[PDB]
Length: 271
Image (cartoon, rainbow, N blue to C red; front, side, top):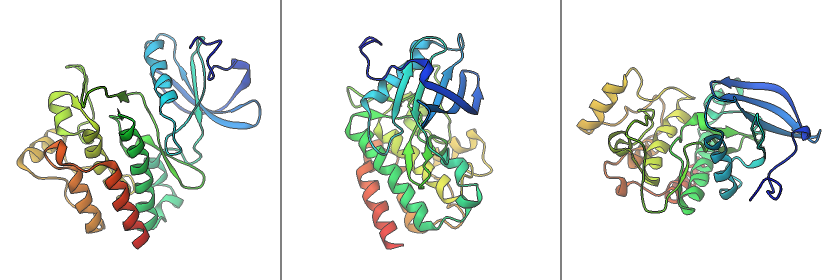
């Protein structure tokens, strides 16, 4: 709908930007307040750094993917500088939170709980026919009550037919990306399942980089031999065998997110 009819458009005067959380080539992320009292995150587009249409495409997708376990779109300001306003998550990205003192003291039970929360968000994305394509701990946000939500929908896509095929030139992080996507540019919800397995390693190692001591060509070489990531230090074997299911060679043999959520809940209610 046009901005004057859109439920998400808000006048820029309703926002006060207070603290800058991040700055990059395409813009900034700030903590701010909407109408004085409601804390929100605001992502601003650096004019000319990228297409405003590409930038807003993420917000349009978020209008269709609303769930408790996904960071919620709050509003948009479509006049330059363009803003996308979202739900504020007090503890920031999971990859950073797990390294703080509070994060370091978490029990394996709480880590399994957070893992199940993320699988629950991804089961919603699965059921709605979308894919995320950038699932990693950096893209999970943590609330003040230690609940987790899926974030960063820039690469997310509605999947009309089972598969999304990227651009031959498009590049993805090798350590988190499924083989079929690295090799063919083909993504399905099963590519996200692979990524989830890698994310589980990030959770259990308190944010360590996957495949320790290995370069990308080494990871590729090992995967092709049938090897998978070495058991992380202090990782429960039940969890490791769940990661292995996510890393099966054939995408169709990998589990669904609903299955992953169900097992992780059992692991938590047990621990």
